[PDB]
Each structure stands twice: as structure tokens, then as C-alpha cells.
Image (cartoon, rainbow, N blue to C red; front, side, top):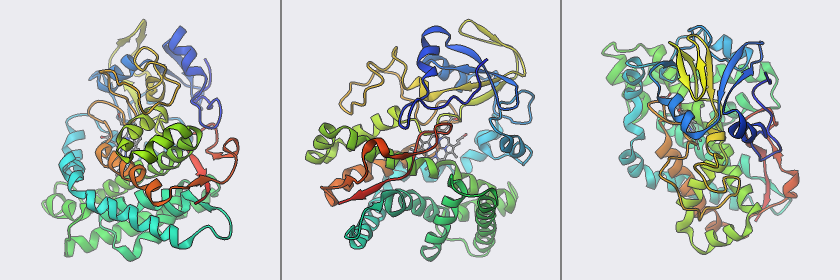
Length: 399
Ligand code: HEM
């Protein structure tokens, strides 16, 4: 059994193993970092089954849960939030924060999303590139999702920049373990302080809703409110940064489609749909353990055996997406959903938010900077290490 996670085939490519497994062995066994064995599911239809089967569990204290690192086995000891829960607990807690993320709520946030993007682009413009390239990640791709989720949680304007850098340090590949843990505690310590303040004087933000509607009536306590706020922060931010950077790199790699996007900014939503299928920057979240024996394809997964369903491979499934390895924002979409945001009850709570952030970004970026250009050769882009989810660490640009 091959060791898993597989490495990406190259900087922007998925692992080469998925295409071969989809063709020859779509439900196979892989070996995890501790020598344990989990099932790997690669085909779109089977990934949807894994994501919705009520015979499967996300509870990480169950036997056989497929932790992918030693830190994850550590994290499995802490008290879970809704990301690691089964029904009925899952939606009991998830419903406490879902109202901010509904399509209607995200619709009403569009002026604020646009303002945030415009303000950051104008800061980047004033900073300029007169003395050499600037890092699009630091100047733009990082602060856009960071400022938005922090503002939704309840962080005041004056605290955004410091917390944005601390959260970035938390996952930066160049941080020592001590640096990352320190930044992590800085975030937890801050959210505790913010929860205490909103318990005394609530405002119009997610933490205040948790404090008034759940903490004070005793449905959860204030440490739960911290952990739920921390989840909303860390679950999606690094992925949002990578999606923005990957979108810019993808357009540089496909100049004909960038030309179409410059000539018609209303193509941003279709660009974003294809980006989220083609670059599956969160590909390891659909994990389960079997509560009871369950048949998947031609395999029997035994009770207490672990399962990883690759939505990245599902999104390149040739049976669903014609010519799946070509990036084409003009493609005709089949009836089947692309799975960039997962599937089933646990489907990304922030899917509409994320698509609105990405659509705002790519309908505005080249109107502000029509000559935006990646300043290094595209083959030299500093991607995330191949053993991790696809992404970009830094992206020098001029404009
Ligand atoms: C393009 C950006 C994003 C992508 C591609 C993405 C992708 C995903 C994926 C693949 C999952 C697993 C869903 C499943 O279990 O089937 C997920 C879950 C989740 N995402 Fe995102 N996400 C993004 C942005 C965000 C943002 C911005 C937030 C918070 C503001 C967020 C919060 C969450 C949470 C809390 C969950 C767990 C939901 C649950 O288990 O009920 N994500 N996301």
C-alpha cells in the first residue's frame, strides 16, 4: 500500500496517482504516516457517497479515524466543534453560526466585500512597484479574506493587521514550531478577550450573536464560543489566500482567457467556478471512519476502518468533467456539482461567502490593474511544497 498523502506531480498539478487509480482501482488502500491503513476513494460518484453516507462518522475519537499527521492525533484529544461532529450535534451547533453565511446574508454583504477589495487594491496602487516587484500574497491575497472573516467575527478595524499576520505565521511553511504555536496562542488569547467584551456589550458580529443567543442562555459556554470562532477563522483563510494567488497564476498561464476576462468582467463567476474545480486547494477534509460495514464500489470497508475521499480527484473525474485536466472557464457544466467545497451536510459553511470574495476579486483586479503581470517566470512560481495542498507561498507581481 502506497504512503498517503501522495505528492503533487508538480507545482500546480494534482498527484499523478489519482488518474491511475480512477482508471484501475478507484477504491484502494493507502498507508498513513503511522503505518495504519485507510481506504482512498477517487471517483466523483463515490466521493459523494462517502460525503453523505450515514454509516460513516466524522467523530475523531472513534477507532480507525484517518489522522494524517501526529499533530492531528493530538488535535483529536480536544473538545470538538461542529466540523468533527455527526448528526444531530453537527447541525445543532452549525446552525448557531450559519445565518451569516446564507446566500441572502452574503448578498447583503456584497457592498462591504467590494469596499474591502477596493480599499486593498488602492493601498497596493499607492504603495506601487516602482522599486521592484511586490508580493501579491502579502499585499492583497492575504488581507482580503483575513480582513473579511475577522470583521465578520467582530475584530475592530485597528486590530486587523496584527491578527492577519499572526494567523499567517500560524501556517507559514517557514515558521518554526515555536513560532507557529506562539501565533496560535496569540489568536486564542485574543478571541477569549473579544468574547468577554461582547458578553458585556454585544455588537453586530458573529461572536456577539454567539454570546447573546447561545452563551448567555447556557446552550454553550464562553470557551466553546472561542473554539467556534477560531474554527471559522482557521478553517478557510489559508485556502482563500491560495485560491486568489492560484487564480492570478492560472490567468497568467492562460492569456487567452485573461483577455476574455479583461474584455468582459462579468465572466468572473464562470472563471471562479472553473478555478474551484481545477485547483482543489482543500483536498483532505472529506474523511470518515466506518460505524458499520459498508460497501463502496467493489470493496467492503469494515467497521472502524478509515476512509479519505479525494474531492480533488473527483474534480478531475473524466466521467463527469469532459477534458478535466484543461482549465476552461467557458466549459459547459454537467448536472453533477464540482466538489471544491465538499458535499453533503458538512459542505463548506462559507461556500457562498468564498465565491463572492473570489468573484469580487476577479471582476475588479484587472480593471484596477489592467497590466498586472507575474514578475517571475511562471515555471519559477514558489508553490506550496508538493506534499501539501496546492497553493502559492508568494507571488511577485508588477503592474
Ligand atoms: C475557496 C475557499 C474555500 C474552499 C475551497 C473551502 C473548502 C472546504 C471544503 C472542501 C470543506 C469540507 C466540506 C465537507 O466536509 O464536505 C470545507 C468545510 C468547511 N469550511 Fe471551507 N472552504 C473555503 C473557504 C472557507 C471560509 C472562507 C470559511 C470561513 C469563513 C470556511 C469554513 C469552513 C468550515 C467551518 C467548514 C466545516 C463545515 C462542516 O463540517 O460543517 N471555508 N471547506
